[PDB]
Amino acid sequence: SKLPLLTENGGRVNRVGFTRLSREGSIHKFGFFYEFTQESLDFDSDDQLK
Amino acid sequence: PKNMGKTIKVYEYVPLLDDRNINDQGIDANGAHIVNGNLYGSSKDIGTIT
Image (cartoon, rainbow over all chains, first blue to last red; front, side, top):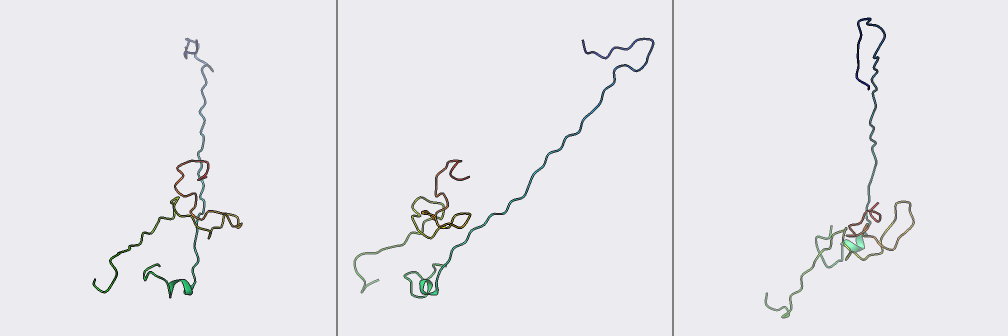
Protein backbone atom coordinates (compact mmCIF):
# COMPACT_ATOMS: atom_id res chain seq x y z
CA SER A 1 0.00 0.00 0.00
CA LYS A 2 2.69 2.51 1.02
CA LEU A 3 5.23 1.72 -1.71
CA PRO A 4 6.55 4.85 -3.48
CA LEU A 5 5.06 4.52 -6.96
CA LEU A 6 5.79 7.00 -9.75
CA THR A 7 3.91 7.64 -12.97
CA GLU A 8 4.95 9.22 -16.25
CA ASN A 9 3.54 12.56 -15.10
CA GLY A 10 6.28 12.95 -12.51
CA GLY A 11 5.29 15.59 -9.99
CA ARG A 12 4.91 16.40 -6.30
CA VAL A 13 4.41 12.82 -5.13
CA ASN A 14 6.00 10.68 -2.41
CA ARG A 15 7.45 13.36 -0.12
CA VAL A 16 9.46 12.15 2.88
CA GLY A 17 10.90 14.00 5.86
CA PHE A 18 13.40 13.05 8.54
CA THR A 19 13.61 13.72 12.28
CA ARG A 20 16.53 14.18 14.67
CA LEU A 21 16.25 13.40 18.38
CA SER A 22 18.64 13.95 21.30
CA ARG A 23 19.88 12.05 24.36
CA GLU A 24 21.08 13.70 27.57
CA GLY A 25 23.02 12.76 30.69
CA SER A 26 23.79 14.62 33.90
CA ILE A 27 26.53 14.85 36.54
CA HIS A 28 26.01 14.24 40.26
CA LYS A 29 28.16 14.75 43.36
CA PHE A 30 28.68 12.23 46.18
CA GLY A 31 30.86 12.03 49.28
CA PHE A 32 31.23 11.02 52.93
CA PHE A 33 33.65 11.37 55.84
CA TYR A 34 34.35 10.33 59.43
CA GLU A 35 35.73 12.12 62.49
CA PHE A 36 38.28 11.11 65.12
CA THR A 37 39.91 12.72 68.14
CA GLN A 38 43.58 12.91 69.06
CA GLU A 39 42.58 11.08 72.24
CA SER A 40 41.46 8.26 69.92
CA LEU A 41 44.70 7.92 67.93
CA ASP A 42 47.24 8.78 70.64
CA PHE A 43 46.38 6.28 73.38
CA ASP A 44 44.61 3.55 71.42
CA SER A 45 45.34 -0.17 71.23
CA ASP A 46 46.44 -0.15 67.58
CA ASP A 47 49.33 1.88 66.19
CA GLN A 48 48.09 2.10 62.58
CA LEU A 49 44.39 2.87 63.01
CA LYS A 50 44.62 5.76 60.52
CA PRO B 1 57.49 -14.46 72.24
CA LYS B 2 58.26 -15.61 75.76
CA ASN B 3 57.14 -13.62 78.85
CA MET B 4 53.67 -13.20 77.34
CA GLY B 5 50.68 -15.38 78.11
CA LYS B 6 49.77 -18.60 76.30
CA THR B 7 46.98 -16.84 74.36
CA ILE B 8 47.51 -14.85 71.16
CA LYS B 9 44.86 -12.39 69.98
CA VAL B 10 44.75 -10.72 66.57
CA TYR B 11 42.54 -7.91 65.30
CA GLU B 12 40.15 -7.89 62.34
CA TYR B 13 39.04 -4.68 60.62
CA VAL B 14 35.54 -4.80 59.11
CA PRO B 15 34.76 -2.96 55.85
CA LEU B 16 32.58 0.14 55.85
CA LEU B 17 30.02 -1.62 53.64
CA ASP B 18 29.41 -4.62 55.91
CA ASP B 19 26.53 -5.62 58.16
CA ARG B 20 29.00 -6.28 60.99
CA ASN B 21 29.73 -2.52 61.02
CA ILE B 22 27.22 -1.90 63.81
CA ASN B 23 28.12 1.63 64.91
CA ASP B 24 26.48 4.89 65.98
CA GLN B 25 28.58 7.56 64.25
CA GLY B 26 26.21 8.05 61.33
CA ILE B 27 24.71 11.06 59.54
CA ASP B 28 22.18 10.70 56.75
CA ALA B 29 22.34 12.66 53.51
CA ASN B 30 20.36 15.59 54.94
CA GLY B 31 21.94 15.97 58.38
CA ALA B 32 19.84 14.03 60.88
CA HIS B 33 21.72 11.35 62.77
CA ILE B 34 20.72 7.79 61.89
CA VAL B 35 20.95 4.46 63.69
CA ASN B 36 23.34 2.80 61.26
CA GLY B 37 26.65 4.19 60.06
CA ASN B 38 27.69 1.46 57.63
CA LEU B 39 26.00 3.09 54.61
CA TYR B 40 23.39 0.37 53.88
CA GLY B 41 25.93 -2.30 54.87
CA SER B 42 25.92 -5.33 52.59
CA SER B 43 22.20 -5.35 51.69
CA LYS B 44 22.37 -6.18 47.98
CA ASP B 45 18.95 -4.61 47.32
CA ILE B 46 18.06 -1.68 45.08
CA GLY B 47 15.61 0.24 47.24
CA THR B 48 17.78 0.50 50.34
CA ILE B 49 20.92 1.49 48.44
CA THR B 50 19.06 4.12 46.43
